[PDB]
Amino acid sequence: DSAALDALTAENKKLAKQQLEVLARYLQVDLNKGAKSF
Amino acid sequence: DSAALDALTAENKKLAKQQLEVLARYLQVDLNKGAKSF
Amino acid sequence: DSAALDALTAENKKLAKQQLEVLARYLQVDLNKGAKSF
Image 1 (spheres, each protein chain N blue to C red):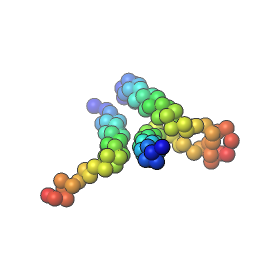
Image 2 (image 1 turned 180 degrees about the vertical axis):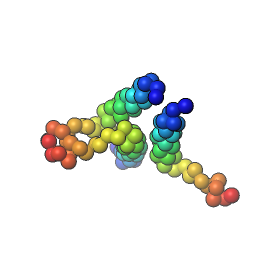
Image 3 (image 1 turned 90 degrees about the vertical axis):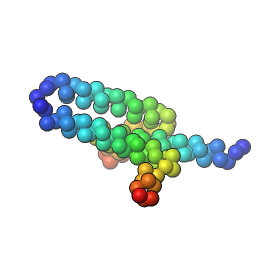
Image 4 (image 1 turned 45 degrees about the vertical axis):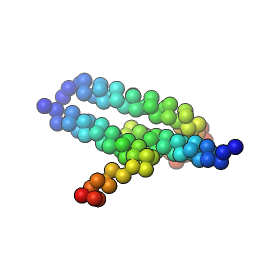
């Protein structure tokens, strides 16, 4: 029940989020065009 | 005017696409929820 | 003794496994040619 394991999981997810961001930015892919149309 | 440079660019973009795919899959992030709602 | 830390480790290893998979797929590298010959 370490309420720090959750933190490092959140950190890893944040790292992955950032990586996804720049990947998409490279691909000229909008991650929200679906949301804009919605 | 090498119509193979375009190919390797397409290959790199495909690699990046795949990487983005598995990244999102890790993040439990739907890339089409916007499109579903739309 | 959190039997969830092991889980997130397994998740990270699965992410890395997948990334390795698509990397190899890009490199046209068989990860089992050794095993086939064996």
